[PDB]
Amino acid sequence: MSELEKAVVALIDVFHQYSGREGDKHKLKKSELKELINNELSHFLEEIKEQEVVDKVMETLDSDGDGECDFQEFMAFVAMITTACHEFFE
Amino acid sequence: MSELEKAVVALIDVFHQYSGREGDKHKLKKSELKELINNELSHFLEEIKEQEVVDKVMETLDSDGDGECDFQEFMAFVAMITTACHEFFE
Ligand SMILES: *c1c(O)c(OC)c(OC)c(O)c1[C@@H](CC)c1ccccc1
Ligand SMILES: *c1c(O)c(OC)c(OC)c(O)c1[C@@H](CC)c1ccccc1
Ligand SMILES: [Ca+2]
Ligand SMILES: [Ca+2]
Ligand SMILES: [Ca+2]
Ligand SMILES: [Ca+2]
């Protein structure tokens, strides 16, 4: 596998890890999203401790309004982060 | 680094590898995009041999119409692939 292919499988993998935990196994509810961010982006994002922040983040990512973050909304999240990092460095 | 963080840095890294080669070092012209797909997605995508395919792919990815693929359009490409892979498996 190339680095890129590895990156794609890792994205799918981490999403699966967190989404399968509770309820809809293909969507991230607030607690799952909070755990993903806290455990997997601890070097990029501030750790979420407040409900207000979990709610704001979910609201921002929840494009279809079903209260959860699906795979597409997750990829939209990944793109926001990756694009911010990219613009940041040059 | 988490798997996810590694994934983000890899995305940025591969884009940088191919974009810096020629012309605008922050954008993928057709030849660069072709080489990225051929060398880095050889297990997910058919190898591109025809100009018609390079042109179709570029056209599809080129949202702002500047003839090249920037980082955002690239992330849109990554999302298409990753989302197709994800839907494919469950
Ligand atoms: C984002 C990425 O991708 C990154 O690469 C490893 C690094 O570290 C070199 C970061 O610090 C970030 C950070 C800040 C630059 C970031 C995360 C989310 C949104 C904007 C920036
Ligand atoms: C997508 C992924 O993630 C994958 O895992 C490595 C494999 O290989 C087992 C694929 O073949 C794909 C395919 C769909 C099955 C794909 C490739 C590019 C774009 C969309 C889907
Ligand atoms: Ca879930
Ligand atoms: Ca949603
Ligand atoms: Ca270039
Ligand atoms: Ca463009």
Image (spheres, coloured by chain):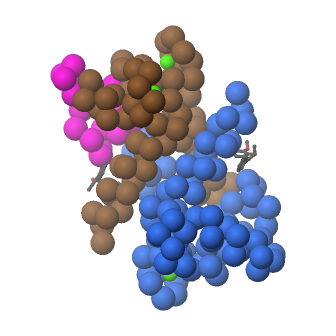
Chain colours: A blue, B brown
The answer to whether any part of residue B39 appears in the image is: no
Residue that appears at 75% across and 58% down: A45
Q: Is residue A38 above or below residue B59?
A: below
Estimate the x, y position of residue B30 in percent, counting from the top left.
36, 20
Q: Quadrant of residue A57?
A: bottom right
Magenta residues, as a range? B34-53
From what the image shows, is residue A37 above or below residue B83? below
Q: Position of residue A31 (x, y in %)?
A: 64, 81
Residue name at image x 44 percent, y 21 percent: B66
Give A81 or A21, whichever is nearer the viewer: A81
Quadrant placement of the N terminus of chain B: bottom right
Q: State left or right for residue B7 relative to residue A81.
A: left
Q: Is residue B78 left or right of residue A17?
A: left
Side of B20 where A24 appears, left or right: left
Which residue occupies the extreme top position in the image? B23
Residue A72 visible in the displayed image: yes
Where is residue B41? Give x, y as percent. Answer: 35, 39
Q: Is residue B41 above or below residue A81?
A: above
Q: Image point 62% across, 64% down: which residue? A: A60
Q: Position of residue B21 (x, y in %)?
A: 51, 16
Residue A43 located left or right of residue B28: right
Image-quarter location of ligand 6: top left
**Where is residue A25, by image quadrant?**
bottom left
Q: Is-magenta flag for residue B52?
A: yes
